[PDB]
Image (tube, coloured by chain):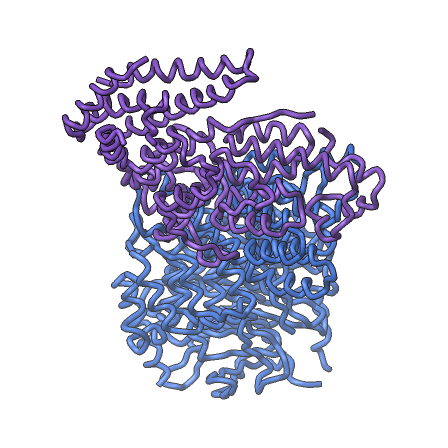
Chain colours: A purple, B blue
């Protein structure tokens, strides 16, 4: 009996209130309505993390595939560790929330070939060996480029990303971004024959990762470009590139913790990774999510204060209940108070329709009182 | 001058020699090693003694000799004492050839003369005697020989005459004599000698030596078919040839020329013969002259021991008993422990047309013959490779599907091959990495070692990063990457860009096809071994799309290969699966690069593992060769074992029987718990021979 039938209609209006800004915003209403589109994006994270409950988990267990050494256990080691997959569910939710701009650049390195003796050099890679023989205009047309790719990779539009990094004749680049999308080899693996139909992956990605990271820390090349590489490996994007942080410092610092356990996992099984394949060192960070939302809290310009962002914080930690009980304490005191902000109490009825529905894990007193006081103080 | 003779003959065991020179005398010798013991001289004759020959040692110690006095004599040894026991002189001219028919025909002798007649005389002290005679030739009969036994109807013998012809006869019941069956007009002068082939294969063989210096070999499959004529070589010999003798095993043809030298000959898959191991007064004048006989009279008849006798002066009787030139050379063969543990890998069963044992089940892999060698001798390379290509890989832990057990086997064998191309190409590339002041070229080379690891690691130390990442996209045959490579390069052309030569090549290894691309790599023929070029299309080529066999082939279609390379040829087999047998004959027809022992172990291990298609006819051919090789080397044990792998039952019997009868005291308990018994050799065969030799050593001691 999905309770979200009412919520879905809050989330619906929340989103349609995002569209009243485009027309004639430009006053306090473009700002206050940045709160509405934040609610909606919260009702979604809520709508889909709760959904996460028992669902034919038994026959899911794939057991005729282990020992495979197929190096593609993502399908399994993201199905057995329900914790990590939960992380992921958040990421995909964050990805559908990134911005995506578009700006007017083809024929790759144009003005540098025509003029520069870079003809002997010829290729990007073979260039870093010469330091400062990148000419002007080119070094900029390439810059805007990796600003469009970093922005678009963040959003997880990988597909549409390579379709553009090709249109600029920057194919050598595009190639690299194929180790990230595939990041492992699916071939004649039984349980998966219904999807791929052909061998479409790249072995030794655990080895390739430590390569692209060696690329991100060389620093000789573009700031943004240098940044997109690190993402695909780990979360140390160049600080000169960390200016922007919607909640992307979230999306990334998490990818850190995920593609790490992922690595330390296929390592634990000795199934996909050779010992001599690890060229560059990489630490196994136990970045517990509860500690990651905290180190990210110092990069929250009061972005961890907002009503809605305190809530997305608990929804992530499953400590949503203690939040509703720590809140009632205030509504009993009446002694200022965030529950006098027009937006927070519509979310107290969130905790009113879920708790009883999902587990019935919330007191009938803590509930009952905040049903009353709400329907009481309305305008 | 010095001791000069005309003919000589060893017996069934080769411990008794005989010589007959123009001194009208014979000389019987007791041969024991490199020594020659004279027993007695024979004074019987009135003219130059031409030839001699022993009769089967189941009739006693007998010797026949003919001379210019047209009188054939029969000598016998009684408790040591030599004595003329009979006489046969029914010819008006001089007698020439004397040979005892196979023992199955009883004590029977053949005799040819210059009067143009041939006679067959039956000697039995108790039994009845009935002589025969035939007008064979026009100007005379120089020689005649008995055909191998097969009902007295299948008795045939070939004759040669100074009328330039080679006639064949057959014992007819009706006529009470030998009627004419075939004439063969292939010479243009005096036929000096004709010998029938003791071989047992479906085809019969005949060798006719001429005075016009030619030599024809006649073959026949069917029993009433046409005798196919075939010159030994399209050009005529130096001098005039005299003798023509076959080896009891292997179908070898020793030939005695007028250039005082003897020249051996063997056959091929073609039928055209390639040469085997080379080795080396008063009233008497007219006699020699009416015999159109020169002063250069050499001779060479094979012995029961498949050994070759030839006149020299190195010996107390100018008769060397050299051992055949065993071209085949392998160290581990001479070992008894190899034979022993090699039999066990077999399940021996007797055939359905005779008790004679023949292999039914074989688990012989190439791996086996690797422990008995060194990891250095050139062979180990030739062998271990075959052991990785054609040897049926096995996967320890079974798996859900039969396709999965396949692709895994497809893979494990793939890695063995490439991990070997490394071991060999090793020194070639390793030394080509010293000569380099181009760190990037140091990469492309390190990639020919299938070492992406130390390759990409280097790419970074090269101060350039990107390629280091693309190097890691190597082993896997991702399609979208093979696509991009070709797209990146096509956008190099239009750009008029100048990419470092060895960096665009690394890029060409991603397009899954480097030797045919836009930026092709065929150029690399110049400095890089053909093998190494192959190693590329094997590691970075389209592993998954094609079949490991097919793929290896799609590289040959790009290059010719060392026309005379053992390892190089091996691949060419692996290459064409459906026509592997068609190409094996196509190979040996052009190059003696695969060992005689190899051709067998190769076609035999492949036929007992269900790897490829093999004609019995062919299998036998290379089994004959190898069976003889060991035999010439005197290893009758291992020789016997190989003979087992014979598919023609009528052939095996003759090969096995004869090999055992002659060499029994060497095939006894003293060697590995009765080797002959562990092979399922007929009980009656042993007993027939055991007491045969005992009959001999009695008369001798």
Question: Does B318 appear above or below B561?
Answer: below
Residue situated furthest left in the rendering: A364
Residue B273 as seen in the image, left or right of residue B328 = right
- Residue B253: name its quadrant: bottom right
Where is residue B74 shown, x and y percent of the image?
A: 46, 73
Q: Quadrant of the C terminus of chain B?
A: bottom left
In terms of depth relative to the viewer, which is nearer, A69 or B291?
A69
Q: Quadrant of the N terminus of chain B?
A: bottom right
Where is residue A258 shown, x and y percent of the image?
A: 40, 43
- Residue A335: name its quadrant: top left
Does residue B137 appear in this view? no
Q: Residue at x 40, y 35 (%)?
A: A305
Does residue B57 appear in this view? yes
Question: Does A377 appear above or below B428?
Answer: above
Q: Residue at x 51, y 65 (%)?
A: B380
Where is residue A290 shown, x and y percent of the image?
A: 34, 43
Residue situated furthest right in the rendering: A115
In terms of depth relative to the viewer, which is nearer, A109 or B656?
A109
């Amino acid at each position: 009996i999905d309770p979200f039938n009412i919520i879905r209609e809050f989330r619906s209006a929340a989103g349609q209130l995002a569209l009243d800004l485009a027309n004639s915003g430009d006053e306090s209403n473009v700002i206050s309505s940045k709160d509405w589109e934040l609610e909606a994006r919260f009702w979604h994270l809520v709508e889909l993390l709760l959904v996460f409950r028992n669902a034919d988990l038994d026959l899911d267990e794939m057991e005729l595939h282990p020992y495979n050494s197929r190096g593609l256990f993502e399908k399994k080691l993201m199905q057995d560790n329900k914790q990590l997959y939960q992380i992921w569910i958040v990421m995909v939710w964050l990805k559908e929330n990134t911005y995506v701009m578009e700006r007017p650049p083809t024929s790759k390195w144009l003005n540098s070939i025509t003029s520069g003796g870079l003809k002997s050099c010829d290729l990007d890679f073979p260039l870093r060996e010469n330091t400062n023989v990148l000419d002007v205009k080119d070094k900029e047309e390439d810059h805007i480029f990796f600003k469009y790719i970093y922005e678009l990779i963040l959003a997880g539009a990988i597909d549409e990303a390579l379709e553009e990094a090709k249109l600029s004749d920057n194919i050598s680049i595009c190639m690299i971004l194929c180790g990230i999308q595939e990041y492992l080899n699916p071939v004649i693996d039984t349980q998966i024959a219904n999807e791929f139909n052909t061998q479409q992956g790249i072995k030794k990605h655990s080895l390739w990762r430590r390569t692209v990271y060696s690329l991100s820390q060389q620093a000789g090349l573009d700031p943004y470009e240098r940044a997109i590489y690190s993402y695909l490996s780990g979360a140390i994007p160049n600080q000169e590139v960390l200016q922007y942080s919607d909640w992307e410092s979230d999306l990334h610092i998490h990818l850190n913790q995920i593609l790490q356990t992922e690595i330390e996992n296929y390592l634990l099984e000795n199934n996909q990774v050779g010992t001599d394949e690890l060229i560059l060192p990489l630490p196994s960070h136990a970045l517990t999510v509860q500690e990651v939302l905290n180190r990210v809290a110092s990069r929250h310009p009061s972005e961890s204060e907002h009503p809605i962002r305190v809530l997305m914080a608990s929804v992530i930690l499953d400590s949503l209940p203690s939040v509703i009980h720590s809140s009632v304490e205030m509504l009993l005191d009446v002694v200022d108070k965030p529950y006098l902000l027009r937006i927070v109490t519509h979310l107290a009825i969130c905790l009113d329709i879920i708790n009883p529905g999902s587990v019935e894990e919330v007191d009938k007193s803590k509930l009952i009182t905040t049903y009353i006081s709400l329907l009481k103080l309305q305008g | 001058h010095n001791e000069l003779i005309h003919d000589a003959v060893l017996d069934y065991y080769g411990k008794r020699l005989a010589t007959c020179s123009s001194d009208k005398t014979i000389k019987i010798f007791e041969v024991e090693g490199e020594t020659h013991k004279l027993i007695d001289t024979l004074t019987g004759h009135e003219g130059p003694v031409w030839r001699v020959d022993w009769a089967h040692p189941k009739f006693g110690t007998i010797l026949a000799s003919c001379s210019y006095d047209g009188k054939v004599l029969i000598w016998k040894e009684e408790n040591g004492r030599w004595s003329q026991i009979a006489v046969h002189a029914v010819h008006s001219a001089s007698v020439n050839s004397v040979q005892w028919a196979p023992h199955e025909y009883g004590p029977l002798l053949l005799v040819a003369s210059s009067d143009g007649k041939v006679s067959v005389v039956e000697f039995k002290e108790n039994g009845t005697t009935s002589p025969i005679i035939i007008d064979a030739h026009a100007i005379g009969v120089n020689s005649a020989s008995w055909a191998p036994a097969t009902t007295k109807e299948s008795r045939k013998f070939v004759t040669g005459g100074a009328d330039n012809l080679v006639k064949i006869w057959k014992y007819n019941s009706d006529a009470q004599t030998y009627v004419l069956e075939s004439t063969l007009e292939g010479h243009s002068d005096w036929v000096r000698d004709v010998a029938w082939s003791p071989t047992v294969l479906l085809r019969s063989y005949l060798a006719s030596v001429s005075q016009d210096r030619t030599c024809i070999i006649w073959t026949q499959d069917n029993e009433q078919g046409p005798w196919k004529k075939t010159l030994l070589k399209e050009e005529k010999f130096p001098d005039v040839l005299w003798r023509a003798s076959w080896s009891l095993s292997g179908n070898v043809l020793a030939l005695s020329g007028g250039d005082n030298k003897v020249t051996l000959w063997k056959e091929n898959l073609e039928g055209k013969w390639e040469p085997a191991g080379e080795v080396h007064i008063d009233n008497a004048k007219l006699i020699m002259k009416e015999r159109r006989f020169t002063a250069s009279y050499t001779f060479a008849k094979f012995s029961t021991g498949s050994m070759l006798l030839t006149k020299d002066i190195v010996g107390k009787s100018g008769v060397s008993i050299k051992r055949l030139p065993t071209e085949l050379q392998r160290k581990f063969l001479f070992d008894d422990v190899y034979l022993d543990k090699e039999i066990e890998k077999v399940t021996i069963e007797a055939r359905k047309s005779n008790p004679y044992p023949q292999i039914s089940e074989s688990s012989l892999l190439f791996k086996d013959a690797l422990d008995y060698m060194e990891k250095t001798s050139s062979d180990y390379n030739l062998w271990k490779l075959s052991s990785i290509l054609f040897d049926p890989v096995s996967y320890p832990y079974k798996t859900d599907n039969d396709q999965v057990k396949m692709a895994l086997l497809k893979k494990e064998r793939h890695c063995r091959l490439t991990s070997w191309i490394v071991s060999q190409i090793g020194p070639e590339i390793e030394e080509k990495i010293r000569n380099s002041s181009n760190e990037i070229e140091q990469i492309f080379l390190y990639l020919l070692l299938n070492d992406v690891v130390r390759a990409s690691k280097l790419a970074i130390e090269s101060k350039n990063g990107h390629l280091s990442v693309l190097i890691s996209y190597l082993g896997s045959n991702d399609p979208r990457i093979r696509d991009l490579a070709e797209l990146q390069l096509q956008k190099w052309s239009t750009g008029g860009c100048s990419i470092d030569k060895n960096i665009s090549k690394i890029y060409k290894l991603l397009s899954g096809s480097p030797f045919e691309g836009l930026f092709s790599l065929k150029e690399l023929e110049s400095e890089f071994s053909w093998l190494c070029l192959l190693n590329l299309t094997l590691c970075y080529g389209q592993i998954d799309e094609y079949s490991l066999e097919s793929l290896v082939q799609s590289h040959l279609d790009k290059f010719s290969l060392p026309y005379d390379d053992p390892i190089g040829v091996i691949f060419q087999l692996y290459a064409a699966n459906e026509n592997t047998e068609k190409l094996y004959k196509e190979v040996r027809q052009r190059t003696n690069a695969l060992d005689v022992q190899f051709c067998w172990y190769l076609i035999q291990t492949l036929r007992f593992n269900g790897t490829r298609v093999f004609s019995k006819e062919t299998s036998d051919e290379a089994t004959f060769a190898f069976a003889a090789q060991l035999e010439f080397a005197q290893l009758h044990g291992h020789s016997l074992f190989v003979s087992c792998f014979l598919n023609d039952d009528k052939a095996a019997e003759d090969t096995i029987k004869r090999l055992v009868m002659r060499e029994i005291t060497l095939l006894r308990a003293s060697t590995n718990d009765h080797i002959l018994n562990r092979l399922k050799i007929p009980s009656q065969l042993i007993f027939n021979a055991q007491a045969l030799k005992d009959r001999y050593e009695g008369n001798y001691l």
